[PDB]
Length: 170
Length: 106
Length: 50
Ligand SMILES: *[C@@H]1O[C@H](CO)[C@@H](O[C@@H]2O[C@H](CO)[C@@H](O)[C@H](O)[C@H]2NC(C)=O)[C@H](O)[C@H]1NC(C)=O
Ligand SMILES: *[C@@H]1O[C@H](CO)[C@@H](O[C@@H]2O[C@H](CO)[C@@H](O)[C@H](O)[C@H]2NC(C)=O)[C@H](O)[C@H]1NC(C)=O
Ligand SMILES: *[C@@H]1O[C@H](CO)[C@@H](O[C@@H]2O[C@H](CO)[C@@H](O)[C@H](O)[C@H]2NC(C)=O)[C@H](O)[C@H]1NC(C)=O
Ligand SMILES: *[C@@H]1O[C@H](CO)[C@@H](O[C@@H]2O[C@H](CO)[C@@H](O)[C@H](O)[C@H]2NC(C)=O)[C@H](O)[C@H]1NC(C)=O
Ligand SMILES: *[C@@H]1O[C@H](CO)[C@@H](O[C@@H]2O[C@H](CO)[C@@H](O)[C@H](O)[C@H]2NC(C)=O)[C@H](O)[C@H]1NC(C)=O
Ligand SMILES: *[C@@H]1O[C@H](CO)[C@@H](O)[C@H](O)[C@H]1NC(C)=O
Image (cartoon, rainbow over all chains, first blue to last red; front, side, top):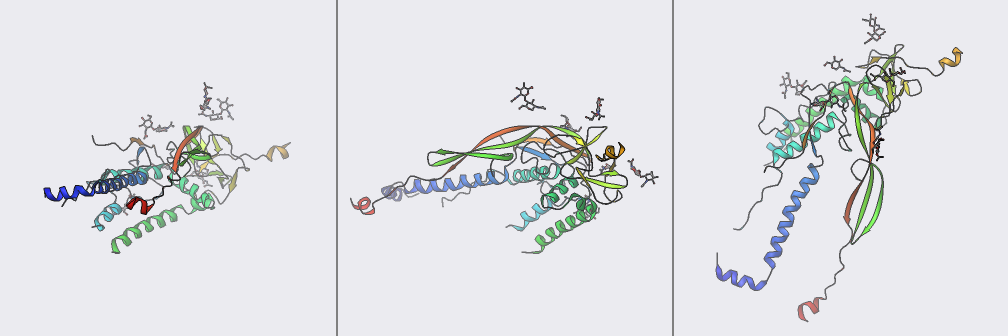
């Protein structure tokens, strides 16, 4: 609040304008980064009420209805595990909207595969989508269909191990 | 990476201190519902599509390519056999045509 | 206002239904990427001292 200090500071020119402009550029760049990462779909996809995906369980990654924040258990664990003229500007996208974007991406990739990323979301059964992914890596569809229960059990076990590993590693 | 949609090609254009890429992509449109099955049960054998997918318009079963609707008769030339019908969940019963059958029939 | 992320689109998922495209659109999109800047040189002695 010193007037004499500001009068002497004016002798140095537009240094303050340069610093404010650089900080403003960084601040808008962070919002641009968040838009580029999370806002890649213009449709908010939602999962069907019946979670019949041929044995595949997505409860640990889909949003929890019981939580007011509408986050997944994994996302909730992630949020729990992260702890003089200065101002902190809030991010343009809040945490619930970022969670909504991730939920839309999850719903699109579960119900439609990769179709929603290239155009209109085309529905496909999830085992058939997994079979398409199997064909992408050079494994025949029959292998997926014959061992579908085993593949679903392995996927659920791996997702649970991911949650346990995140909860058990500082 | 090269535009929204399935990338077909791209064209470069010079710009002042920059480049403009015109990405030509293929976008699916006018989609239609069909009833689908993982495999076709015929003669106690399970048939799977070689490159396409089994679709049904309500009464008849066909095999088509995944990115464009082009229904074709389910034959032995576009399907492959792996195992019986007891293992695959959701297998449906439909006939599988044999192109060689009229040749020895005549 | 509170911004809207996108229009809601509930995909009609079921265990035995697929959506197959019957047509296509050849879509051309633009992507602008900067390549170079203006090449500026400053004579340090002449700038500071003339
Ligand atoms: C999907 O997985 C979730 C969690 O892995 C299962 O929910 C569990 O259900 C059992 C039995 O009802 C409960 O004892 C557990 O406490 C539940 N866990 C959680 C985290 O809620 C769920 O049953 C699985 N299957 C389906 C169809 O959702
Ligand atoms: C599903 O498609 C098949 C073949 O495109 C349809 O079968 C044809 O139906 C027309 C109209 O009755 C007949 O004139 C043709 O002779 C049929 N072709 C064959 C090979 O049978 C079938 O009707 C379609 N089903 C529905 C519900 O649209
Ligand atoms: C598809 O065809 C198979 C074989 O023809 C059917 O399986 C038969 O089902 C009847 C009804 O219970 C049994 O009596 C036979 O013994 C079964 N045969 C075999 C080889 O398993 C099957 O039910 C048919 N499915 C549909 C939907 O028509
Ligand atoms: C495929 O069938 C589903 C279910 O019959 C259609 O989904 C419905 O479409 C109507 C049309 O506007 C909506 O009002 C309903 O809310 C939709 N239901 C669900 C659960 O999404 C779907 O539109 C059909 N797709 C095509 C291409 O015909
Ligand atoms: C696929 O969509 C194209 C549009 O790109 C359709 O082409 C149009 O067809 C109508 C009627 O024949 C014409 O009046 C339009 O001028 C055509 N548009 C263009 C850009 O040529 C095409 O007919 C559609 N095909 C199917 C099978 O639905
Ligand atoms: C789809 O689920 C229904 C029960 O909702 C079941 O009767 C039917 O057999 C299932 N179809 C496939 C292909 O899994």
